Length: 94
RNA sequence: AUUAAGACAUUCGUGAGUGAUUUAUUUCCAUGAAGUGGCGU
Image (tube, rainbow, N blue to C red; front, side, top):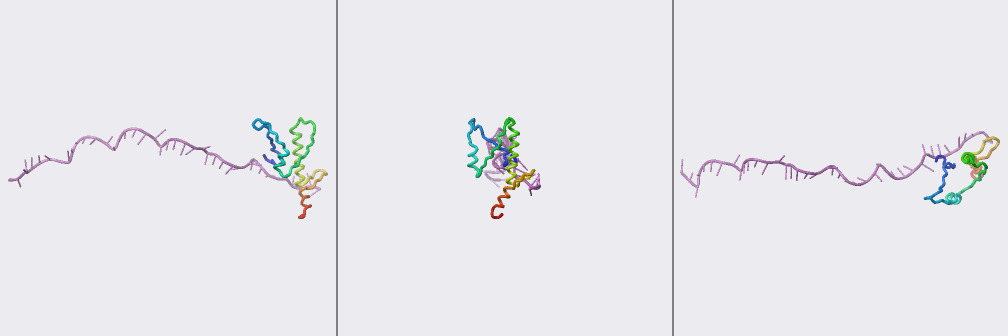
């Protein structure tokens, strides 16, 4: 789908020809990708509004986390420097 | 006046009768409606 790289079209397989699939997500990502990181989302209670409350946190966090590596955060009195910018200052070409 | 004289190889007669330019053949193969955030430090 559109903007798929930010996690908008995630699907998983449940039944293959009426057989329950047991595929560990961690090692499946390990073999296919060079680097894999896991983020612990806040296991807030009232997990009955599964759709909106969880989705809003996850995508706000992704926008938060992605707009840390690329550019920075500039809102209220809270500033995180661009990690990409910090990365290139550290190295030799500066 | 001489084995001679006269005598259309002619009459009638449809190149016609039966016959499907038809049978077989995928306008199909490949292809992300996707990409990116920016400024207010």
